[PDB]
Length: 414
Image 1: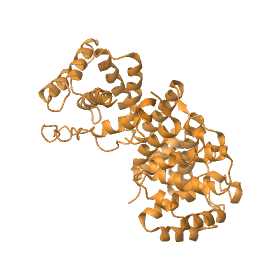
Image 2 (image 1 turned 30 degrees about the vertical axis):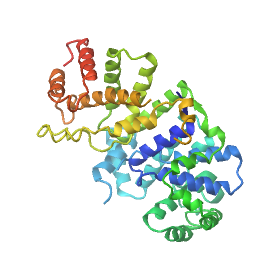
Image 3 (image 1 turned 120 degrees about the vertical axis):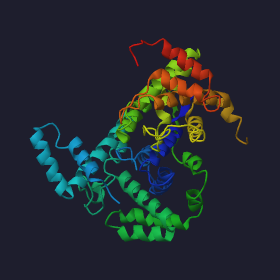
Image 4 (image 1 turned 90 degrees about the vertical axis):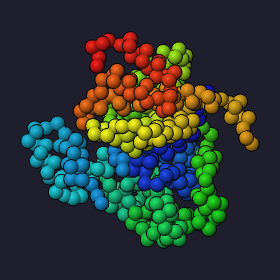
């Protein structure tokens, strides 16, 4: 099978959205709003393409997941980013200086985020315009935005559309369009480009734009917006790119669990080898293993870690971890053209196999590793818990394969 670029981005974008995203398909809605604003400025097709992605990828930078930030969190951030690579003593003094104002911190935060997101865009082989324009998202019309304090048309057009689009959605959904329309009107000339604001003003008159915003299938409709260029099929090389890029995003978003994705991928491949899965399937499986983690900032299975608890029954239900895994995989996995064609009115098994393997790995990791707070479970102990708990919650073609695979490993490894 294959993926379309637009399609995969939306999916990945939506998921990473759930962390800090704010609302369930926030990015999707901005795209829809932003494309529509753009659509009315008579942009070139390339611009509309670049805009489409800028809108989708605006939050790529965000290193946060989610009455304010913890002091610790704040300090940790300053340290870890600045002061960078100087006497210890300097770093403390510098971090203190930032902490105290104002301001300064906020500037650091944006600069980091904006630079980081711009970096993602580049990694993903979008144009500099896209990267620049994720970077200036937080500039303001009046020259009061960060991090560069650009004003007016110093600001890239995409950022202007994007920021405006973004704010509007948040209001749109927190209150009432009219409230939203009002709010943006309020910031016109301050945060926003007045001209753009006007446009939104029109769109609102235009129903069907509204219908589209409040549609269940909005994700499908957004797809129809861009130029065809957005729909490129993804080859293997690009996929590596996406995965590799996103993995960095995940590692940044959840520091505490880092290396969890890699481990699961490893277990997953090991199980797969045992099942004599094909080379190609394995390749998906390894990517899938990392990707399925996106979102899933929700606690694992199941608190867990917690040394104390960790007894049965209560997680018999919690086993519907996917559940989510299956759904996400289906959205993720490569697809068959004839199959997609043959459903314009109105694979399943594989997903189940995939889900079972990855899920089994996911469970095995959860029992082991229990590393922070430190508490690794012995491999064979963890293996025993599954079989102890199973047929009920544990596949068993995989469980065997897991065991067989682990067996081959050096026994040094506990």
